[PDB]
Structure formats: C-alpha cells, structure tokens
Length: 264
Length: 53
Image (cartoon, rainbow over all chains, first blue to last red):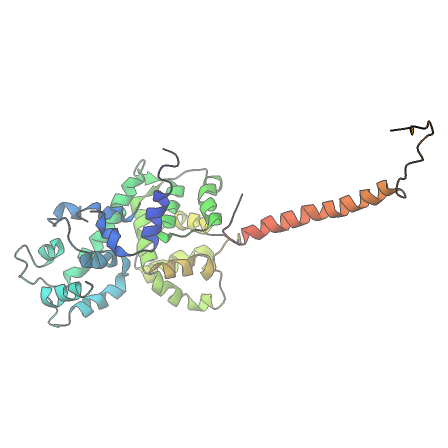
C-alpha cells in the first residue's frame, strides 16, 4: 500500500495540524483520541461519545504549559474556596456548544475534591500520551534512534519545511555511532519544550543578539526555566537537527519561535 | 541539385564571414549563463521549502 494513504496520513496530519474539532472528535473519543499523534486510560470509565468540550479541555491538559495552567486552575476557581464543582465547570463546558468528573468529583460526581489535584492529573496525562508515543517508536533496549527522538520533535512541531525534514533523515550521517534515546531523556526535554514560553523570555537578552547560547548553557538555562535536567548528547542532536543555517547554533527564527507559535 | 538542368553549375554557396567562430562565441557565453542561472536558482530553492536534493 504505497500511495493508498500517504494522502490521508498527511491529511489527518493536516487536520491535526490546524482544523475544526468537529470531525476531530467524530472519529469515535472513548480512547480513539490517541489518534491525536498519527495507564490513565485504564482508569477511564468514560462514555464513548464523551464530549468535545472536555476534548478542548483535554488537549489543553497537554497544551497549557506548567506555570500557566495554575491560572487556568485559578480561573477554574471562580467560586474561590480552592474548589469548584461542575456548576461553573460544566457550564463553561457547555458554553462552547464525564470520566474526568468521575475521576475528579468521584463516581458520585458530587463530592468536590480539592482542585489542586488538577496539577498531578495534568502531570500523568502529559506523561502517558508521551509514554504511549514512545512505544509507537518501538524503543529498542528501552531506547529509540536519534532520528526517532528527532522525528517526534517534528511530529511535535508539525512544520512543513523540506530542508529540516531532510535534516531529520540526514542525521544518521551526522550520528552513525548510535546511542539510543531513553524515555526519560526525552520526557525531561519536552517538559522544557512545554515551558518554552518563558525560555525566550528568559532568553530575551540573547534574543536581542541571537545564537541561542551555544547549546550548552542552553541546556543549563533549560533546567533553570524547565525545573528539570537534560543530558548533553540529548540536545546536541537537536542543535544538529535544527541547524538549518549550518552556523552550529540557533536563531529564534531557527528553533525557538517555531516552538513558541506551536502553542496555537 | 548540384547542376542546373541546362548543364551549367550552380553558383558558389555563401557562408557567413567565419561564422563558425561567430556561433562558437554565442553558444558558450550563453552556455556559461546556463551554469549560473541553474546553480543560482537551485540554491535559491534552499532559501525556501519548495525543493531540496
């Protein structure tokens, strides 16, 4: 099946790139939502046609970065008292036009848990979707190829540029040694890739000149802004991948900005 | 035909003033441009996402 689906494989990608959520959730939703790529769900006592409002909520549980969703948490708390049940919740769910409620407010749906549990819930979901995707790339020895670890970035970025696309292919020439990329050395990077919004902010002085800080303190300032450490080699391939200009560094227009605008 | 029907011989055909060197220096200067506007154009496709080797 050569050219059977290399239109829909790009089309569904184009849908998942930028499109309306209507057909997006029509692909039932119970767990088909994992199609959003290309152990929480065991606890998903959901109802197949759940909603698209929760969907809008759901992707934001992966879209909203770390420090910001605290405000979404606060915005969720219009009743104050550190807690808000479905009254405000399901209302702002309705304004667009269940398992999470059973997961938050219990199967009774009434007992209002501390909405501080919005964070940890956001933590594992970001992990699980990243987890399942890590198996989709078939981690050999618990590790994946640098062209896979770079591939998911492209799958994350969702950009259409033939050059860097080929650079993703050409990396085996730039990296023929082979090390494999573990699930932890990629999860830490995405948490950084999540909080990109503040990095460029923290990097503004560099942004006033450029070069994205020589790839090493980049990793250092990453841990500062991202609250999580990365290794050295993990980012060397990233700078090797996105070095479109061949300068050995990045401009904001090289790597950062594309990430920044990705939050659309 | 080489000879006319009367039996005479057709006149001398007319070349053009060592045109062989004239053409030879209208092909090459427009052949060298062939290399340029190709290489320049392909490199111009590196500037964008239209194509890449």
